[PDB]
Length: 146
Length: 146
Image 1 (tube, each protein chain N blue to C red):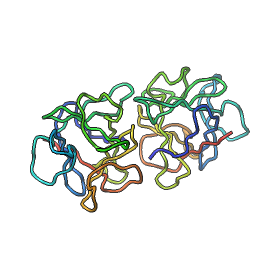
Image 2: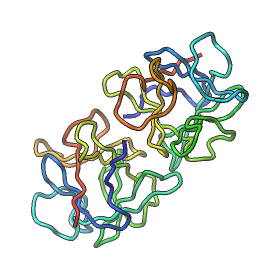
Image 3: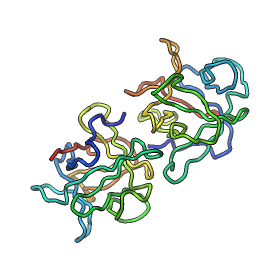
Image 4: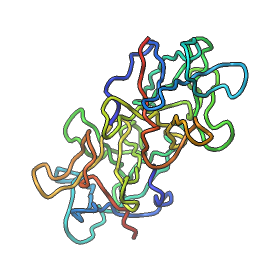
């Protein structure tokens, strides 16, 4: 079931992992351009959503406030999770926010094109990335309204 | 995770519920035109898949062999589950097959447009339909090869 509290189009937020408490950033300098961070608020941690319509109904593009690039999640080449300019030109720029089966307050950031979810962990490298498989708690996220 | 053994494009199959053992049919006369059946093979139980591409990658239209109509699953009006002419003109004509978390051999028939899955039960009316909510075993299906 879709997460029932998805921010309105244009509303700004951070994406913070439930368990690690790390946030996603999306920048233009110093690859990897998309990763996780444990520290103070910076603008490259700020996103809004582009609402999908038509074939993209119930999907969203995740767009950087400062640089305007949207996130992508793919399995075909490195980097697997990255950014690209536009408003969701490519199918792997589109995400579904799927409510957790157990914790109604969190969701997975799911990619239809690549059948992956994003994760954040403190354990094995790579500690941030995408994943196709069983549901684990390190795949759970919050919208943190700013 | 997408179901890993989805029939090749154009290959014919039935959809049988894991628990009830009932099959979906899709006909043109005598409503409800899409429902479940507990008996021997008839041609209206035969379907093929149109493979989605682009925005519909990992989605599929479910097309009836004898009558050519595709299935839809919606929450907006009755019938909630039905059929319609064409090859998937509308976003609610497209389905994802999502493998169960515990049983690798069954899946849910999921509609991205409507956030629903199809179900089959023997308990209360309506015994066949769609549903938005938690996961139950009566939502689990098999591809039956012919």
